[PDB]
Every structure is written in structure tokens, then in C-alpha cells.
Image (cartoon, grey):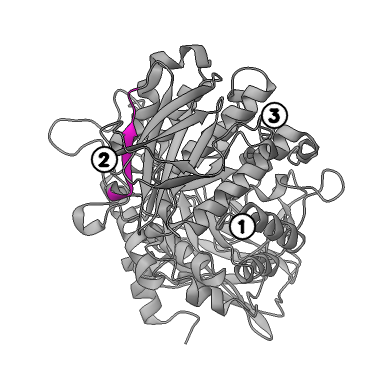
Amino acid sequence: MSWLTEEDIRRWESGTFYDSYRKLGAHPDDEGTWFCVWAPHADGVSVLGAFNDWNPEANPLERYGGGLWAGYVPGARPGHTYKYRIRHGFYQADKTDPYAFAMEPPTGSPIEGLASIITRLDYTWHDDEWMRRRKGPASLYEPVSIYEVHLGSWRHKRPGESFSYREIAEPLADYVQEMGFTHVELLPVMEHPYYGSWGYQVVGYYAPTFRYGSPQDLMYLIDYLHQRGIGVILDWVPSHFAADPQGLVFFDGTTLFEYDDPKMRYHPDWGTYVFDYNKPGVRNFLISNALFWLEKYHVDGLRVDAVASMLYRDYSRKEWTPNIFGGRENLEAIDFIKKFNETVYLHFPEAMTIAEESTAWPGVSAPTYNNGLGFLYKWNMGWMHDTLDYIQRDPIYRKYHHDELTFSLWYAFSEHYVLPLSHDEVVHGKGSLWGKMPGDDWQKAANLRLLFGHMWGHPGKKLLFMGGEFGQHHEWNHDTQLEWHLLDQPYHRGIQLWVCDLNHLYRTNPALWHDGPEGFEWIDFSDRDQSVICYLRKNAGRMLLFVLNFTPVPREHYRVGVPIGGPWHEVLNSDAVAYGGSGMGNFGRVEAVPESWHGRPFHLELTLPPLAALILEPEHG
């Protein structure tokens, strides 16, 4: 007889209500709006909005089972702003809607206020074909090349003003299409008061914002990218929420969304920060939100950061405590992750879930029925550290650190990996990708191409943060746009054209699509003295040879074992003049010699250009 059915209430309090945004939040009809809030310890809840005059006594919600409050408001219309007054004993606080589907332009109080917005999510999609063929499967055996994008700081329309969700669609799509990426990965779009947070704090999990436009503007952006053949992955932040006073903290006068406190007359005060993954309402709130992005915004993937902060509760010397009653591991959090992944693939097979986990937890990307966390992909952070360590060393000392370059193949196959050069690596004291490279300007440029050559040959899918693809000079600055003027310089234009030609090779040559052991075999890793390595990528009857010269010394008559005789050809050469290189290479037919090298039947005899990546293939046509 009310907003809520008895089945809604059973499902909420057992924590099996995974479409709870159907009923929680603000739901307009043709005449008024239903409001519904979880607040099991409040003594009263009222809805304050433009439609009364923010009168806490105009519309006091009634309480239902499971700690849910609900109330109808006639004449509350889409576009009205509103807030909740929560009363707990003698304390009273105004709160934004946790389930807000939009939050008003003032969306801090530094910003000029903060109210949620009554909204309908109505939108007509035109992306049926993408969603059918998006059988985005085991993309495990296909090319996946991700362009990582913070929306606001990519390009600016006139000065310090970002493009909108609608205004960014066409230039972003054009660029991603010419650069040859398959996907765009977006830093959190969920509403956040601090822009400088990059989105990772988050007060509005169900609200795409109003900073780049409305909910339907972002839908148009995703609809538009889908029709241009580009997938979209959303960074998603279940590990913690913003500490802002109007967000989820406290909420009903107690620890609701965060963990509850022990006895605290001194005693190591450990409490909160993460979500309380053992409250049924929290599992409803987060699992509902993952499905919400997948269903209401057609997104193709979710990436979870800081999975280590969820798996462990460690912090300190002395925090939970040891003995023989538990471990360092957050048991309910591991169960939440596994329920998260297995719900996503049940409801949205061939969506992608991706994890960044920084403690070498086994089986991050392994099925939950083998004690895995259930993700499709794991960020290869180990590969990133070793590669950025080695490449940063001046070439004269690289011969003493050859192991830093060949080590990642030891562990390259223990997960399904994305090889990522993310935004985290080009901020704070770390330098841009260009700035990390040693030597003179041409050597910086060649090192960045050599780095990309190796990254695309190394097993794993690919992710690069915006700006990195043309060797931007400075660290990423979220308050400005990227340094696009550098595309008038030949070394940066040349780096961009080479990433583009790498992407094209990745997408048209199956030799690079199988990232498991069968897909890679060493040709030689023993040349420490000259800092060279050779290796094969191998899939469906196709083969590419990678030869990588990590010193600015050209090598003539350099012999390389190959397993197939006959005429070979250079497919890509990072010293081509088009990329800013000097134009050395192995041109025309390269005939394989029927003598033996590297324990191989045949060998090629090549010129290795300085700081260059060579990619060759046998003639099979």
C-alpha cells in the first residue's frame, strides 16, 4: 500500500537487492516524486527541496521495515533540487541523496551549495549493434588497447573550460579512432566535490555529475562512442568514499556506510575509511551501483583501484591482532569482491572487470570457483616498475641491469594482464613519460618509442594515459588541458605517429592477440653487454619477431636466430624518419641464412638502429 513491497524489504535487509536504485533515491512520476532513504537509526527524516521552501516540517518521510524511510511529495518535479534532514536524538544534519541520480551545479559548498536533482533517466539508445557485437568476450584472445582519459583535462574549449560530455564526443572519438585504440577508460565520473581528487573521493555513486553535463549528456557520449566502434571503461571506487560532511559519513547519526567502533577509552582506535562490507545495506548499495553503471549507461567495463586496501586491513604494527582467530585478510571484503564479479558476468556477460592490486595476491583474475577474485584483467604493476626502472637508467649502465628488463617474463602469465602506463605514473614527483627518459632530446624520444615498441610486444593488453602518446613534457596537470601544441614539434608528432602505427599493427595482426605462454617465446635474452633482446610473438598461423636495441650504439651485422627460413620483411621500424628517427633499417627482402644462431635453424643478419625497436615477419603470401 506504500512505496515498498514486502519483497523489497526482505531483499534489502538480507542484502540481495541488487537493483535497489529502482526504489531508493528520488523517483518522479507525472505529478510528484517518491523519496526513499536508508537510515535505520534516525528518529526522523524529512525531504527539503525547492518545492516546499526547504521547510524541514513540510514533508516528513515515514518509516518502513529494514531501516528504510519513504514519502511522496506532490508537485516535486524533475529539475527540483532537494536534500534530506536526518534527525538522530538531539543531533540533526542535512545530507545529499546517496542514490542521487544527479547533483546540482553547486556540488560542493566550495562550488556554491549542494543539492541532489530529481531526474528521470529517460534516453533512447542507438547502439544496439555495438551492444550485440560487443560480445567483448574472452577479449583475452583479441586486441585490447586502452586510452586512459581524465575528461576535464584532455582538451579545453576556449580557456580553463572543459568540453562537455556532448562536445567531447566527436573530437575524442576522432582522436581515439586515428590513434587506433579499442577503448577509452575514464577516471571516475561519479560525483566528487574536489576536482583535484581526480574523481577518486566520490560523494555521489549514482550521479555522473553536472560538471561536464547531465546524465543524458554522458549517455549521449557513450552512445556516440559505441556507434564509432569504441568501448568505454569506467573507473569505479568501492574501496572508500569521500569524507565530506554532506556525503555518506555517519549519515543516520551512527556508523552506517563505514565500519563501527570498538571500545575507545584510548585503545588503538581502528575504525572506518572503507565501506562496511558486512552490512547488507552496503552490499546492496555497491553491487546495485555496479549494475547501475552497466545497465543505465551501457558501459563496457569497470576498473577497481586499490584492491589491496580492500583485501587487507593491515595499516600498522598492531591493529586487528594475530593469535589463532583470523588473519590480516578482510574476509567480508574478499567475499564482496567475489560476489561483485560473479554478479557482473551473470547479468552482463562480456562486460569487463579490471583490478589494480599491488601486493601480488594470487589469482586476482582467476575464477571464483578456484579461490580467485573473479576479475577479467589485472594491471601488471610489476612489469611497469621494472620497465620504468630500467628505461630510466642511463644507457651506459643498462648492461648492469639486464635482469630488470627480462624479469617480467617470469611472471607475465600468472594472470590475465593489462600492461598499464597510467596517470598515477606522471604526477607528483615522478615526471612525465618523456621527462623520465634519459639523455638528449632525440634520445628521450627514441627511448619512448623503444619503450612503446616493447610494451606492445610484451604479453598483455595495453593501457596508456593521455599525453603519453606524444611524449608531453610536463607531468599531467588536472587544472589545465594537455600540451597539444607540442604536436608541431617533430619528435612529439613522431612519437604520436608511432603509437598510431603500433595500434594498427596490434589490431590487424593476430600474432599479438594471445598473451598466454603459447604466444611468446624467447629468441635471446643473454646480450647483457649490448643491452639487446630478441623475442617472438606467435598466435594463429602468424609470427612477429621483436628486436630491441636499448643503447644508442648502432649494431651492424647483428645476427638473430629465426625458426622459419625464407625472405623476411621489416613491418615496423622506430628509427624511420617519419617517427623522428634517423632512417636506419633493413629494407626490401631480408633473406634468412641457413646457418644456425641462437639454437635456431636459420638466422637473420640485421642493422640495429640506435635506441630502436625492430618488428619483422616472415613472408607468407
Mark toward the viewer: 3 or 2: 3
Query: In the image, which residues are magenta?
Result: 518-526
| Residue 271, above or below 509 | above
- Circle 3 packing at 10 Å, graded few (<14), some (14-19), many (20+), is some
Residue 191 sits inside the magenta stretch: no
Marks 3 and 1, Cα distance to the nearest angstrom? Answer: 37 Å
Q: Nearer the viewer, residue 66 or 444?
A: 444
Query: Disc 3 to disc 2, how far (Cα)?
Result: 39 Å
Q: Position of residue 434 (x, y in %)?
A: 63, 28
- The reply, left or right, for residue 389 in relation to residue 266 is right
Mark 2 lies on residue: 329
- Residue position marked by numbered label 1 in the rendering: 96
Q: Amino acid at mark 1?
A: Thr
Q: Nearer the viewer, residue 171 or 443?
A: 443
Residue under the point 45% across and 45% down: 568
Q: Which mark is residue 197?
A: none
Of labels 1 and 2, earlier in sequence is 1
Name of the residue lying farthest toward the right: 158
x and y, in percent, of residue 348 in the image: 41, 70
Residue linked to disc 3? 474
